[PDB]
Image (cartoon, rainbow over all chains, first blue to last red; front, side, top):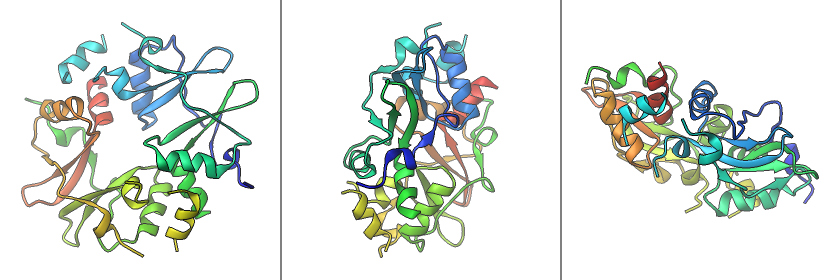
Length: 132
Length: 132
């Protein structure tokens, strides 16, 4: 495989992450502001520690007033899905594509040799890669 | 219910739709360009005729070269999910929220009295509504 994940992933600076210390409130606000459905969760050393989505934050697994009240408090660390499935930068693009097409996963976190979160490869990234 | 769906939905002009005549190619390209996972499908009279997502277009329900080849041809009309669940503009926001929180649906199409697609209400729209 000559194409790598690092060539088509979403870069670190352009990522919107969240820490386990983050409150559900500001997490939801970040979701709204950045038009997203979830983020990866990192620690202070920028190492991936989990994944968290809207259904985790709103605790769906309930209605409007429940959210009204919810936003008035548990944290991301207690709601996030810990230790997701991960790829690297040097990872062949076709393998990541295999995951993102044979499974129900749309997003795979991309880390480096030290476990530091350095990006995110999405299904849309793969489609774009096929288009470019 | 005093809050309505039309107050917090995604407006018509700001929508990214697709017709059944649309090819899978340009659909995927629109997905990439607009950072989205799917669109509502309308006819020429702007009436909602279906819904289509990335998994429908890539026919996941497979790998990178399969997409390579796929983009070189069936159309949206043969892949879209026809006649989705719908809300109106005058629809109470709390009911739509009930749907978007008690179910696995993140997006509900918003039509008018004539069946014309006039918007889209999302889970993020509900969260934002709770934040505003």
